[PDB]
Amino acid sequence: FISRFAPDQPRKGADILVEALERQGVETVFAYPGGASMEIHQALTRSSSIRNVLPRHEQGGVFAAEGYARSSGKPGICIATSGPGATNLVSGLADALLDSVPLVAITGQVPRRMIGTDAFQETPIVEVTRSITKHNYLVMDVEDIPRIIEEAFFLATSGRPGPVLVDVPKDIQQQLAIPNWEQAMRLPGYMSRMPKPPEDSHLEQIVRLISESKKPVLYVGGGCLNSSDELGRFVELTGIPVATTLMGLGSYPCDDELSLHMLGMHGTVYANYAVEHSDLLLAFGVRFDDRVTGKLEAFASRAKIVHIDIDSAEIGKNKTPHVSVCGDVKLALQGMNKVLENRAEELKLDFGVWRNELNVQKQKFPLSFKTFGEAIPPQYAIKVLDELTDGKAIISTGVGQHQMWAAQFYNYKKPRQWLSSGGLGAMGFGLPAAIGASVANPDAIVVDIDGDGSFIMNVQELATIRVENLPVKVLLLNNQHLGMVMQWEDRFYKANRAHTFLGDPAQEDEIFPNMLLFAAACGIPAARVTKKADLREAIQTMLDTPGPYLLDVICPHQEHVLPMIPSGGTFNDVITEGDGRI
Amino acid sequence: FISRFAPDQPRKGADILVEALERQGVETVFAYPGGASMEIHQALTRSSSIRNVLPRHEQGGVFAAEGYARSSGKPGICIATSGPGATNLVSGLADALLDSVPLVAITGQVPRRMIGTDAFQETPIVEVTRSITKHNYLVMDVEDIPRIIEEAFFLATSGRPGPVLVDVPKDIQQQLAIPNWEQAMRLPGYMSRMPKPPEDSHLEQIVRLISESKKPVLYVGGGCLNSSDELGRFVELTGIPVATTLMGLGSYPCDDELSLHMLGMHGTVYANYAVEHSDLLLAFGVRFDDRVTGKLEAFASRAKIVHIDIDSAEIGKNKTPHVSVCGDVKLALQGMNKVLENRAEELKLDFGVWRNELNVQKQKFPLSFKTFGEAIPPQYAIKVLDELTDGKAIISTGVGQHQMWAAQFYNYKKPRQWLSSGGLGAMGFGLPAAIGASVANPDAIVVDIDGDGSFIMNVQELATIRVENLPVKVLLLNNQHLGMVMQWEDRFYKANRAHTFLGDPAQEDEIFPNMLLFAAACGIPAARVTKKADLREAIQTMLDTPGPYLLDVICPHQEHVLPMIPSGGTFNDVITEGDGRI
Ligand SMILES: CC1=C(CCOP(=O)(O)OP(=O)(O)O)S/C(=C(\C)O)N1Cc1cnc(C)nc1N
Ligand SMILES: CC1=C(CCOP(=O)(O)OP(=O)(O)O)S/C(=C(\C)O)N1Cc1cnc(C)nc1N
Ligand SMILES: Cc1ccnc(NC(=O)NS(=O)(=O)c2ccccc2[N+](=O)[O-])n1
Ligand SMILES: Cc1ccnc(NC(=O)NS(=O)(=O)c2ccccc2[N+](=O)[O-])n1
Ligand SMILES: [Mg+2]
Ligand SMILES: [Mg+2]
């Protein structure tokens, strides 16, 4: 590593922190400047390897860092000033923690001598973010910067990945010092309980259970994002069907005959059927979240549960397993793969009768949508995008109906193609997320499947897309409503509208606001499409036009995401029919 | 009070909470719906007295409630869903606490049985907001709703006003119960240390000090917002000049001969002079914040300090006073006014020599600006707005250069005409704040003096302005930069630009983005003005056109806010000359 400073020569704390980032392999930050972080931004300009993407609001900054992180496997880095800068990161951090996204957040702070005095732009950010980050730090000495950054990146990326925040007082940024880069990390506790490689004692007991079962199911989630090859090989050696959580899409290719697609509340009927009637549940890298389980005692009630997780706090949290393995699923699969490879003819595994039993359910209840006259079905739009991009686009989304359809109707080949807020479910995620994805993946098609409710929340980032000259494609499914809330309104509150309409009550038939004009304000080419016939061409034009593009897709507002298990329900409660129409 | 329910008849917790609001005199909420707050929104629709203004992002919601609160003296109410809804309020709460703004925030939460399980859209909001609210609550029983709401509004509005958050679990919203409205508030500690009326022992000692002083100064702040009459009478009985904090503008009319205008870092030279050389400092409703004091030992170092504050934790926090009074400044002035009225001829007060000494400073160093050819001076634009509105507009602002000029160059007659984020200094405040102001004041001219950096952050609220048909006027001082950061960049970092340019580096002379097109997207009439000559007419057109209006005012980017005391400095360090030019 080549420094920009002599080994014996003092420099500012701000300059130490930036070098600390360079030494971690950081190439991009998302930083919005302010009083308490100016020094860091000054140090940033004199770096040649780190580029800064300036957002227009710091919530854009964080979600952009998440996009960056989710679409690459690298940690996302964002920087903010004290006070209002810092607090605007809060939703992103909470989002990153719940979805296990590696993130390092750096915030400026008032000078140390003023911490606690309610100074200009002061917020006890360490206090505020304690329950919503993996860990955080207040830097109280310039001597500590090398050690804290190293710890921050280590903690953020190791074990169960998560957000780490580092608060840096202005006077520390200014203090001249000589950094020492060979300090030991002060993480003795965390480091002592980092999971060991799985030994064969546990792994052969699982292969034993597989060979003894008649109806096995793979329940696969966000823990498997780095184990696509391993899981691939595991399936071809067992022939066990694969259900997936929303966070796990793409781990196993959605367009394969062994794929049961997504399970859960808006999961496919056949996936939930498989899990309902399975005798062996192989839960790899999941957290038995309420959205997939529903009522707990009814979830895989006839199943022998095997649960592999890198977090011990997750094992036996919601459903208590029969067999458990604590550690990396990649290694567990690698180990299980060898056992299955060696004893292949010794086992002669055949799950034909079970796989077939599922194949009839896949036909009796496949994913379906209605086409009404010339109106665009949102589902069909996503199918056309899938066909035209050849299933190879990076997709980010907002939250709601459109998010579920983007999950249901696009066929993700690899993981890290699907970027979405699952745990927290934060609106205004898709657009800034797309920015991060595109900066991390300069040669890939990046499409933000967004809703008009979500899109508008962080519309200011269209300024960012244009200025940063990024080829973000926006497929806006415009249905004039907060659809997800409207669906629940329709089915539980006698269709009584409670502030879910997003258009203008005066001109109730006019599309409002005009999303094309937002795009024009930022010099981004845009088109609107209303007839289904024009769709195939409109989307093709979006893809072909160089640089950013917005396509406003008008959809009938009364479509419903199906299937649906009402919250806290069972597989028997599954709703497969109906909409907000007549 | 007429209820919508029989006294003996059960109803939902959601319906109890809404009635609790009606019983408090609530007429407006700012609420964005979601999964965990649907029930509240359903209960809201069946209320006939409370209207809901739906924002497009919940940070808009909070700042709108702040606008409402700041421009009326009533508490502002906002409602949000769990998780991402709740976290998006965070900047508003922190803002409201630092500026002492009465606010009640209600958030939905996951059902009680799931608190702590990282459920769908769960955030420990009570944990997160503890250090940034006056108080908060987790409701654990439907029986507690009447008592908690009453406590919430009491705490939010009594003593030193502030934000209070009430977290309400979904199952509590659904539970049927019969509310009891006569419960005693469980605030024995808070209620026992609520300040008593000031007795004459203290007040005559102050009048004694006034008559003994030769160079007295009134240092007046946000504590005086409800004491404009009392302070008015106090001045006409003493003839003591009035300096003001940013939060206190309008308490004493800026356009009066006894007014020293604003003091502090961007305060007038004569105001800071007065305070520097005063022998008696009358600090009424201020908090000796670093922005006005600078280096503490040098601030009024020759002055006898009298400090009246409703918060005992503020008295002797930063500067230790000689004499102090703990309580309401309105009552203290009322008491002091009688003493001064009775002993008028007995004292024969005359501060001519001191007032005159200040009058020469007011001439030697008045507020000034340069006009460059045909380009618009931002200062002059605000002067024209002042003249044309007759000084009677409600003004909200973003944060930065434009905020200081809106403070310096508009002459506020009454308090609660000036709405601005002072303590936290949050960008994207001016626009949603204006919405709250206009909903609270349907017949007043409401103008948001905003900057292009700040404006874009919450540009989505233009959808809100239009749909809610509110006559918000937006005077956008567009200088293509984060000006305040740029000014500091110019004077401390050799003009080295560190991510402060907001336009497009490709088309560097084109105004970017096009703010008129944002306004058009939301069907809001808009015009751009570049030549100074067209300004008088452009602004007049903004005022005359019914409904919302945006005026894009182009300004040379290298203007500097003056005067300026570099942070942590003295009156001797005052900078009165220069800009970002040649
Ligand atoms: C408004 C809303 C939703 C509607 C989103 O509106 P959209 O128009 O963006 O998406 P669509 O459903 O119509 O396709 S879904 C939802 C959930 C699942 O909690 N919420 C509540 C919600 C409210 N606020 C934020 C920041 N995030 C949220 N998820
Ligand atoms: C960007 C910025 C400022 C520039 C604001 O840009 P504007 O264009 O809106 O205003 P102007 O100065 O050019 O007239 S001032 C400032 C301070 C005083 O901390 N910050 C840092 C800042 C950054 N982010 C938020 C939410 N609030 C802030 N105050
Ligand atoms: C652009 C700009 C505007 C206003 N202030 C500043 N910077 C500072 O004030 N720096 S500072 O002196 O260290 C400071 C003193 C008290 C509170 C906060 C800060 N601060 O956040 O930098 N920078
Ligand atoms: C619009 C919409 C979408 C999804 N969910 C919901 N509501 C619920 O799920 N209600 S719920 O069952 O009480 C619930 C269970 C677990 C976590 C969170 C909630 N919740 O926030 O309402 N509402
Ligand atoms: Mg929608
Ligand atoms: Mg500007």
Image (spheres, coloured by chain):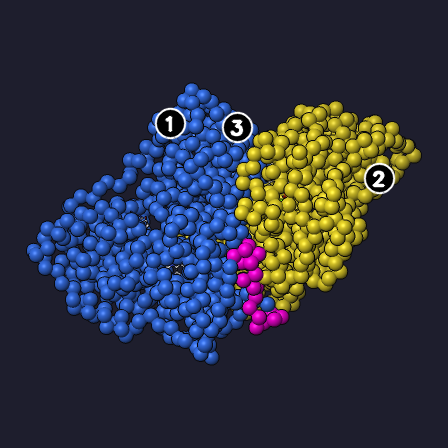
Chain colours: A blue, B yellow
Q: Residue furthest left?
A: A346
Q: Residue at x 61, y 54 (%)?
A: B515
User: What is the secondary structure assignment of the residue under circle 1?
Assistant: loop
Mark 2 vs mark 1, CA separation in Å: 62 Å
Residue sitting nearer the eye, B295 or A359: A359
- Callout 2 amino acid: Glu
Look at the numbered disc 2 and give the secondary structure of its residue: loop
Magenta stretch: dominant secondary structure: loop
State which region is magenta: A505-524
Q: How many C-alpha atoms fall within 10 Å of the one at disc 1: few (<14), some, or many (≥20)?
A: few
Mark 3 → mark 1, Cα distance in angstroms: 19 Å
Residue on which disc 3 sits: A174
**Where does the image place residue A242, in percent across and percent down from the top left?**
25, 60
Residue linked to disc 1: A181
Q: Is residue A114 visible?
A: no
Could you say where residue A565 lies in the image, as x and y percent from the top left? Answer: 36, 67
Question: Are the residues at dot 2 and dot 1 in contact (C-beta closer than 8 Å)?
Answer: no
Residue at the spot of label 2:
B257
Q: Nearer the viewer, residue A132 or B405?
A: B405
- Identified at 56% across, 58% down, the residue is A520
Ligand 3 within 8 Å, label 1 CB: no
Report in which chain the residue with disc 2 lies: B
- Residue kind at label 3, given as amino acid type: Gln
Q: Nearer the viewer, mark 2 or mark 3?
A: 3
Instruction: Name the foreground residue: A442 vs B542.
Output: A442
Furthest residue in direction right, as rendered? B345
Q: Residue at x 67, y 31 (%)?
A: B565
In this rendering, do the residues under marks 2 and 1 share a single chain?
no
**x and y, in percent, of residue A256 in the image:** 25, 63
Mark 3 residue crowding within 10 angstroms, few (<14) / some (14–19) / many (20+) = some
